[PDB]
Amino acid sequence: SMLPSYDFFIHPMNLVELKKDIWSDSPVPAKLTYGKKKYDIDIVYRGAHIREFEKKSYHVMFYKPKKFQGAKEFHLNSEFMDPSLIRNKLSLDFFHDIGVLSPKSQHVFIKINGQIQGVYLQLESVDENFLKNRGLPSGSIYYAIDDDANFSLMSERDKDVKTELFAGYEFKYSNENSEEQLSEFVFQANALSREAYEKEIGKFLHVDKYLRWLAGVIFTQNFDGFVHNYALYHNDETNLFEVIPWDYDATWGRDVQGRPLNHEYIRIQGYNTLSARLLDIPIFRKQYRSILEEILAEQFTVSFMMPKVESLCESIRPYLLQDPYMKEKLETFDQEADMIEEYINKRRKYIQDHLHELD
Ligand SMILES: Nc1ncnc2c1ncn2[C@@H]1O[C@H](COP(=O)(O)O)[C@@H](O)[C@H]1O
Ligand SMILES: [Mg+2]
Ligand SMILES: [Mg+2]
Ligand SMILES: [Mg+2]
Ligand SMILES: [Mg+2]
Ligand SMILES: [Mg+2]
Ligand code: NA
């Protein structure tokens, strides 16, 4: 399980510019060498608080050649907040396994200007190539970027109806209809009555995929996954929206501050207005309960998940010993598998103990 080794060159003049204001989103030119092939790229720091680490995270945009392994860009996360370096990949792959569209990812080993930077998670860009590589129809992709991506009519800050129902999203891949399609979905999700919901919500939303995404938030326990940490995809063939996870490191027993969970938990009904409206419909409540039971029987088990944990950790461990930011804390890293295993057992019990609430 060798990791891909990427060698980046950033000209010293461009590196000075990159380091001058770490908060800038203006990229600089760079080069990537992978094996015997060289790529002209543009590179920029990514994220927010993750820019504060010496092990920076990067957004890589391919310039010439235009594509690398089917993509025009990817994200390189240090995952430094996660002592295991595996929670984000573990989560996103889990969403895929329970039937939700999800970014692919892989661990890589990077150098910049001949200096090892260590183990990174390469994350797929959810864009037009994400769709094309899965054989999915053209459409629109929107990234949840602020508190208005809440599936409600209401702006929390304004304490009023949103000025625009498409507020809260970056239009990553879009067309002339993208704004009105998103506004219509948000509107109908909130404006359809309980008596009309079962018949009509499925004209705008892929309900089974939404409920499977919701289950995924509940199983991984991303406490901020209901109104953040996702993208929307509007499939132009079916005219339906579905939800795609993003940024799932605060999962499997640790919170966004990196702390172990004590007695904190997420109720099985999850959060946000759309979740609430759906779970007021008997057929959708039963559908969701059946999704949870199915996942408890197949995917969210120690026997299924822990071999993946163990395989990921074994693949990266020798490289962590060569990582100047990680070389020291292999022992904490080694203890994360047991923490994740204990989490699975505790979370399974909670969910099983509360399934009756969906009856
Ligand atoms: N699939 C995605 N969903 C949501 N945001 C994304 C996605 N891919 C990249 N981003 C970017 O992620 C940034 C936030 O960083 P992070 O904290 O890593 O989510 C935003 O500026 C988005 O443009
Ligand atoms: Mg991030
Ligand atoms: Mg390009
Ligand atoms: Mg539609
Ligand atoms: Mg985050
Ligand atoms: Mg209710
Ligand atoms: Na973010």
Image (cartoon, rainbow, N blue to C red):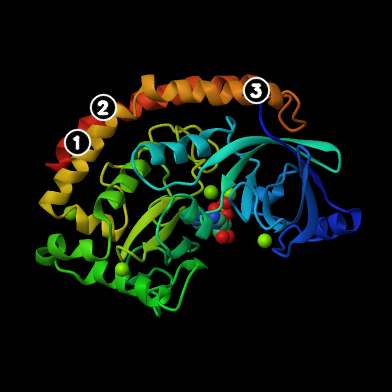
Q: Which of the 4 image quadrants contains residue 233?
A: bottom left
Left or right relative to 101: residue 283? left
Please tell me whether mark 1 sits on a helix, a strand or a loop: helix
Query: Which residue, given by chain and number where applicable, does mark 3 sit on?
Result: 317
Residue 9 coordinates in the image, percent (x, y): 83, 48
Q: Quadrant of the C terminus?
A: top left
Earlier in the chain: of badge 2 and badge 1, it is: 2
Residue 270 coordinates in the image, percent (x, y): 30, 48
Q: Nearer the viewer, residue 68 or 182?
A: 68
Name the amino acid, label 3: Arg
Residue 311 coordinates in the image, percent (x, y): 53, 22
Q: Which of the 4 image quadrants contains residue 156?
A: bottom left
Comparing labels 3 and 1, the label whose residue is closer to the camera: 3
Q: Residue at x 28, y 72 (%)?
A: 187
Please tell me whether mark 2 sits on a helix, a strand or a loop: helix
Residue 102 coordinates in the image, percent (x, y): 44, 46
Earlier in the chain: of badge 3 and badge 1, it is: 3
Label of residue 297 in the image: 2
